[PDB]
Image (cartoon, rainbow, N blue to C red; front, side, top):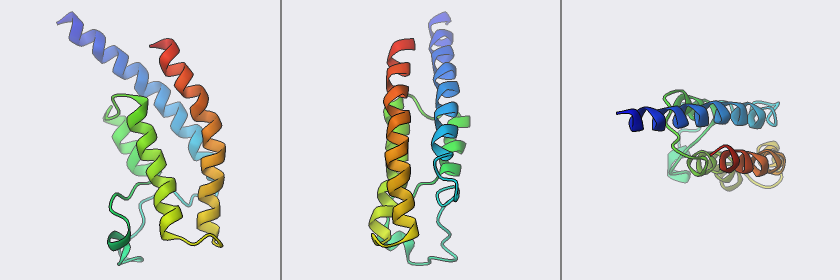
Length: 121
């Protein structure tokens, strides 16, 4: 149906916007602390601590399969990256501090993405 096609075009346009949002967020992590999944080889206890691991590579895989239906979904995954880190790591660590800076800086980006996703529909 043409209605199905049109919905698919909206999903594609969302995916384009989310790809640029994701690049912008990841630039706020120049140390690449959140680039890849936490390794279970190197933190074998991780899943006892953190129930839903998340990282930028995993988000990118989801995005390229057009797996985010809306910005809420995408923000949920971004928040997991930050929130997981601030629970697993202590306040006085380079990891926790990188999460705080990513949150603060990413908040600016997401504030306008929300307007762009609404605005362009």
